[PDB]
Image (cartoon, rainbow, N blue to C red; front, side, top):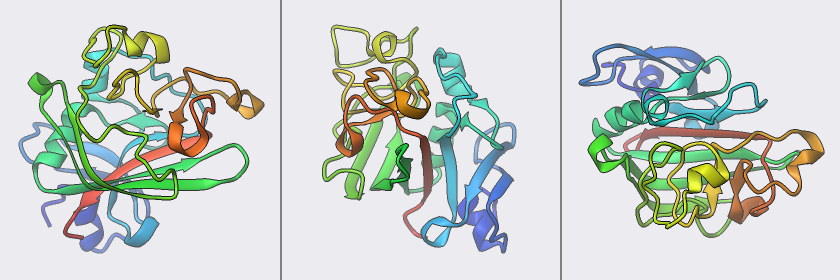
Length: 218
């Protein structure tokens, strides 16, 4: 049915994880995405994935808007596409995380969406659960998206210049999954890495991230 997301992809009989094309309402061009059909019933559209540091996340607003990298590996879907998808119905957000010592954790939000570009792709979440901290490492109560060329944070400083990448930063706040990818034992003592404070703390840089969405009604 209207392949609007990986949930539709899954309902239509494709039960196997991989690259698919989805047709997002009101977007001009189709979009290739990774679909995770494994976690917890499947139907997850991946909006961010990191695992090796091959792809650099130190980009500007335009690139954070339109997306970068490739769905076969590491990528950012793009805010314009995250908006367009999450406009077409109510979606939940799940975030899969792994440290360098083999531990996996996840955070999950019952409700997720972002505003439009004029709203600086502001973030709204509700209903945090999971094994990657009792509190949410993403701020629930509203933060614009910021990049090195768009200072929209709640700080008198510039969080994108200090922590790297593009994220919904507060006083930078308790996360940045789009920070610098550090490898091996370098995961220790890094302040501008790939961080999720309530899981491994402000100094740990994570081994892999996947952020993915699917409809509430799935």
